[PDB]
Image (cartoon, coloured by chain):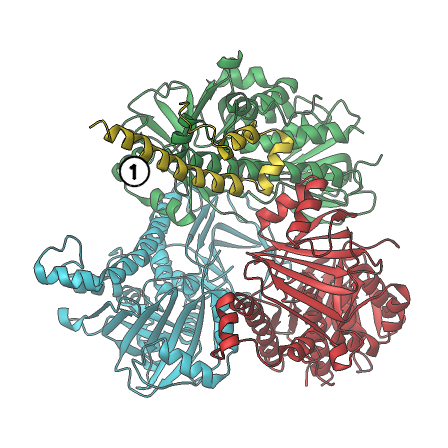
Chain colours: A red, B green, C yellow, D cyan
């Protein structure tokens, strides 16, 4: 066969991030991939922690020179209690909280780095015919009958849900002014992620599958009207430019699986998150920690691995607890609380000061290992 | 290998409907099938649009001469608000709204047509060992190591849900008189589809999985009693003749998937629908439109395909919106509305005239391409 | 005796007012995106009537309810 | 190839139970397995019926001499209505209701019996490459290209859910005194299964996936506190010894699948049950009945099989109806009922005498065939 330390099933953003990173390590890496200039349909909101992973792996400058859309300011509100919280890094001396970046740009960029590295070779278009999990090797095979072996195997970017996300490019009357905006309305959440164009956003609309489907099939003049009302007309009249696309949010009760010489990292790109467009960050953080742990015994044994699994399942509970926490905060910003604030009898409230904590979370400069 | 324009995974009602139809087209078709005279357990309520597909493909006369059970009249009601709507095609000069037809008859009939056509050959009993999706060919293989290639591939009739359907043959005290009847009760819906026997119906009982399971395991005297109460005793005392069978309703948030040289059509035979026994019609309409589109560039490229996908996901949203609409209508037929009708202050009500719109929907003579 | 028939008419009017508030809520909860989809495709069973504008005007003016005279 | 009467996919507790049992029958059995002394994480609460299967197959004495933890007494209560029912076999002359037994012990024991039997051979570590379901043989294959054939095939122990179970070893302040305890709290249920150590229990905590995940990731001092409150402090202060593990409860709407020469028995080890730790018993009862039926025509045909399927789907409805029944009973033990008891106007109540019926259910000495 060919022999590798780690082969990586499904080479998208996160697996390649792993490739460039799990390197200068003494490990040979195989990577299995089983398969324009306009505003992509799919974007991720890449945070400071994620940026420090991509700057480290030497690729930041690349997709910067491509297309990057800095936000330093964020607004979240609730249409039912009228509660709202807004925050900025500028208030704490930061220039940006994150960047909206198109997925195709990110991946095609990490792909270019991949073969610009010699301990990485790229295998495509290749699908798996058989894998016989051996004690010491992976003994996986390919459809083209090329035998393959590996110490540990790791899958990502694919390879149960509650809501779907409808995403699309939307031209707004008023400039978004580089603000990530998020509005809660019942069990709908509607976010506007600012793009390069001063009047264009990529939305993430978390809806029930039935709701997402109806919205996707609505005529456009009705969609335009309906999206803008659900957003409180925050940016005025709305106009869909791109196609409307939906995909299941494959959070929320998973993101990690360790096994005898197998590690699975969740498709964080398609998973729920308190901060819209931020799911992928959870993936980039899975791998950074995995890069860290892997560069040392045997790399594959599911003992030095389940402790890594502990940390990740842990992170997924934290994300769940956080969404629950945003809802508690908004439902608590009601008129009775306003009365009590005034009279000084508040028992439980927004903390001093959650602005700085909201900033450390958006930047995700926690979660980092360092390094 | 053998070379085909289109191979069809899982050759049941819908795929064969596609076979006979996607023909006189210049396309060679392969069809993969991976596997009595009493009243079948499984029946579909075939509408006028579906009839026009089957009459076109030359098969209508066949299963007519077999067994066909014309209904021209329909009754829907709600056990909670006591709302109810009934309608007929006879009122608009039509002889029938649809036909109740046994699935085995339909499929074994389209099967007989299949090999009575030379651009169709039938491959069975055959299961897939490998498929390597090539740029220009399908390069699929068989368990018996027979290599196979195709321009486009299309799967159907199998190959997430909310409710299960319990179906069974039920003898009633009173003749059904060729009326399709449907009763809502909470989140249970119970339909009686009229059969050849003037006193026999095939039911569709949409229940939660837990409810469907209990009903299926109830002793028969209790089932008889329980089915009749849930039906308001509309047809009097009830007696199960056949076995009780349940299957998940694999609607409702899907029915189409397009991909690079792949088209998926939903298992419409097992999918939710406002009109009981009508799911399969959605499938026959998927393929008619697919026959239409396919008979022209390259048949396989996922560009001239996703526009077809748009139309179908669209149709599934329409079906969802319709079920939501039947519930709104029944919950609105309440005593306060009755008072307002009398006094002329109704703002929102059953439209003039939804009888004719209910008939165009039951017949499904919309949805058609023509042709 | 010549009075309870007057009472009938008024309790009646109060039921009508109650039924009307219930009716405004039904109308708003029914103006949702699924209904919008069905309007477009012509499969609406139940909807705002043609034309409730004129009926909304006769109610606001309350030129019903009058005896005349 | 090699020829077998029955091959058994995934040889764990239940399949091996089938192996030893489906024997002295004239049937050759193949068994496919695709893969310490401290208190195991995973335990099952083995009932009297299950014991009579294991005593019959000659293995009881073994895991007895290993580690067995007799309970004869049970307590169930509800934290909301304060309803509660307790019961014992001693009250009806029985020495035990069941035994808490570690899964690894059970399986490694039945494994040892397996090769101590000559009509059983064990195939491992082996995964399936292909199975071509023939009319008379199974024609299955192995990854190591060893052809294999079988009359009937049966899968078990693996090979939709609502709740997850968190399980763990917990040291308690007060001795459990060999009482199986179960507390309902909203849609949480928390059970303590008594172990060898007079102060140690293995819990089963049925929670929503989101709740199970948070509990698993809570710091231990918080978990200790939280587990004890949810248990009404029945055993005082609590201390987790082992790791916290969760797994989806793959009940509740299935446990059997019959097919043309295929029988599936549910992973009863991971399925919901009214009595905590008892799911596996449903599996041992599936196979006893299957041993019974199989030892006679053709063993494989799905005619003499679907009647077996009837019986099992039936048993799963019974289990569902039972959980529904425990909730009705607790919600009905309220103060208004107490008032009516006193005054003699109770219409509906706990039956005389459900203690004896609770004992026949815990022991599961119903469900048995005999034999």
Between D204 and B149, the residue placed more toward the observer is D204
Residue A123 percent location from the top left of the image: 81, 62
Residue farthest toward the front in the current orientation of the protein: C69
Q: Callout 1: few (<14), some (14-19), or many (20+) C-alpha neighbours within 10 Å?
A: some
Residue farthest toward the bottom in the current orientation of the protein: D173
Image: A66 above or below B117: below
**Is residue B150 shown left or right of residue D4?**
right
Image: B197 above or below D317: above
**Is residue D241 shown left or right of residue B250?**
left
Q: Quadrant of the C terminus of chain D?
A: bottom left
Residue A104 percent location from the top left of the image: 81, 59
Q: Quadrant of the N terminus of chain D?
A: bottom right
Q: Quadrant of residue A48?
A: bottom right
Q: Quadrant of residue B288?
A: top right
Residue D78 percent location from the top left of the image: 29, 68
Q: Tally the marks.
A: 1
* Element type where label 1 sits in the image: helix
The subunit letter for the residue under badge 1 reads B
Residue drawn at point x = 53 percent, y = 49 percent: D138
Look at the image and tell me whether residue A270 can be seen.
yes
Between D22 and D90, the residue placed more toward the observer is D90
Label 1, on which residue?
B226
Look at the image and tell me whether residue A2 can be seen.
no
Residue B17 percent location from the top left of the image: 63, 28
Between B345 and B255, the residue placed more toward the observer is B345
């Amino acid at each position: 066969m060919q022999s590798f330390d780690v082969v990586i099933a499904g080479g998208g953003m996160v697996g390649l991030a792993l490739a460039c990173g799990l390197q200068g390590s003494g490990l040979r890496i195989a990577v299995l991939e089983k398969q324009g200039k306009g505003h992509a349909l799919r974007v991720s909101a890449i945070n400071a922690a994620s940026e420090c992973l991509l700057r480290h792996i030497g690729v930041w400058e690349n997709l910067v020179a491509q297309r990057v859309s800095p936000y330093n300011d964020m607004q979240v509100w609730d249409k039912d209690s009228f509660g709202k919280i807004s925050f900025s890094g500028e208030e704490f001396g930061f220039s940006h909280l994150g960047h909206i970046i198109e997925n195709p740009v990110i991946q095609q960029v990490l792909w270019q780095r991949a073969s610009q590295l010699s301990d990485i070779t790229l295998l495509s278009p290749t699908s798996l015919k058989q894998v016989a999990w051996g004690e010491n090797e992976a003994f996986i095979t390919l459809q083209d009958d090329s035998m393959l072996t590996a110490r540990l195997v790791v899958g990502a970017d694919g390879a149960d849900y509650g809501h779907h996300a409808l995403v699309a490019n939307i031209r707004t009357e008023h400039p978004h002014q580089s603000v990530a905006r998020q509005a809660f309305h019942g069990d709908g959440i509607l976010a506007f992620l600012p793009l390069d164009d001063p009047h264009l956003c990529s939305i993430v609309w978390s809806l029930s599958p039935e709701q997402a489907l109806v919205m996707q099939s609505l005529p456009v003049e009705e969609f335009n009207r309906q999206v803008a009302m659900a957003f409180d007309m925050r940016l005025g009249l709305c106009e869909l430019e791109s196609e409307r696309q939906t995909f299941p949010l494959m959070g929320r009760y998973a993101r990690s699986f360790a096994a005898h010489r197998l590690v699975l990292v969740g498709d964080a790109a398609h998973t729920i998150h308190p901060l819209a467009g931020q799911g992928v960050n959870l993936g980039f953080m899975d791998v950074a920690e995995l890069i860290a742990e892997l560069k040392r015994k045997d790399i594959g044994q599911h003992l030095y691995l389940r402790r890594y699994e502990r940390r990740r399942k842990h992170s997924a509970a934290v994300m769940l607890a956080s969404m629950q926490g945003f809802r508690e905060l908004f439902d608590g910003d009601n008129p009775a609380k306003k009365l009590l604030r005034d009279v000084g009898l508040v028992l439980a409230d927004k903390l001093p000061g959650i602005k700085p904590t909201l900033v450390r979370q958006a930047m995700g400069l926690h979660d980092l290992p360092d390094w």
